View 1 (spheres, rainbow, N blue to C red):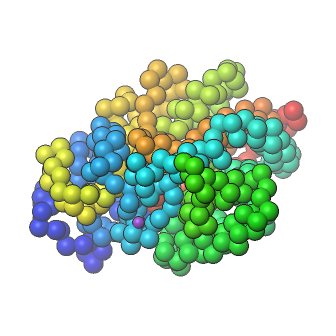
View 2 (tube, helix red, strand yellow; view 1 turned 120 degrees about the vertical axis):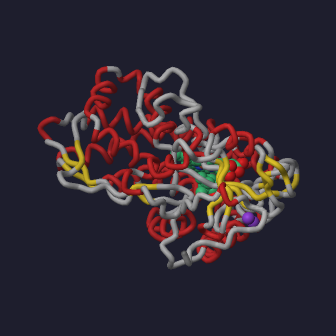
View 3 (cartoon, rainbow, N blue to C red; view 1 turned 90 degrees about the horizontal axis):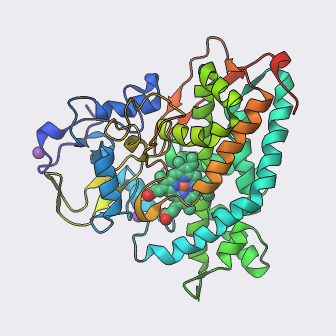
Length: 407
Ligand code: HEM
Ligand SMILES: CC1(C)[C@@H]2CC[C@@]1(C)C(=O)C2
Ligand SMILES: [K+]
Ligand SMILES: [K+]
């Protein structure tokens, strides 16, 4: 096929599995199901796909976790597939490896960490409620557009002190970096995001506010002033994290709940199980998949990896691995040991995971208490999309207003 890069001389012929992370063949069964094909009976722990330029793929949690822990061999310098995107990718602190990464990660943690989340609690609560109550009497909604996007994005824009009217442009840009449609290369989308930030960063370094951008722009890294370029590379990352993570996850979760009245009932009858349900949904509907680049020739699990080789280490796959969780595709809110790497693993563990969990738990609680019974619009053929971050194209929901409650 013209979409297959010639197999490099060092890659064993028997390890070839032409998986396309941007258009997996079994996508119609669900994106997680599509990626799970990499864990079928006769698929090795480590395979090579000739798609998207050619790269390795660790298919089991054991190797995914090991690779993410070994930053000396598996560098974050070129973390995205295809290589062109990975090479243009220079966000901070994600494109850096420890020890260099740390001073910047500390600053980022200060702007989106737990302390910040705690302060945002009220506003997160208020927005969730206002959005749901407004939808409640209508008996229907386009979940992706009416809640999944506005809820987490507005909260991020509030945190970043950015005009909500700027969302359409920024969201288009972020999506081109995670699930490109062809209109822009990763490099072009990144350049536009940086172009957007440059004057805002300059403005806030002159007259700082209390928003995340001002904090980053006027911050220090281990005692010395952060530069304008560094602030830009950090703020670009924050924007992507805030506009294309939780937004997609909420849709996967709500699609599932709309299709499973039993699970909805469980959370309605036992509201205290919501935090645990949140973690199980994070495992079952994990959605991120980036990777690393080999810093030198290295034998890993009996496979000769060559310097420069890219390896996709799907955060999504660890928790779906039957070797980590029995009956992985089954959603069990009572699951005893919820194992996963949905928020990454190693030195780059997600900094916004605390904000993410709050947004998810608040959504589940506030939605179920107002709209306890809902379902997918009759006949709707839900479509998923695959990429660095997978998502749901559209999620039409319906419900009888008579069954709702105006809390
Ligand atoms: C469902 C929600 C989320 C998921 C599944 C998710 C997942 C991840 C993953 C897998 C990584 C590490 C990638 C790597 O190792 O290369 C990461 C890093 C990060 N995430 Fe999230 N994230 C979520 C929400 C957020 C939010 C809301 C923000 C806030 C802006 C955010 C900010 C970050 C930052 C700053 C990093 C980089 C940390 C570093 O490189 O050291 N994330 N996230
Ligand atoms: C892989 C990620 C989820 C992580 C936060 C946004 C993201 C797309 C990155 O570029 C680093
Ligand atoms: K070969
Ligand atoms: K790079």
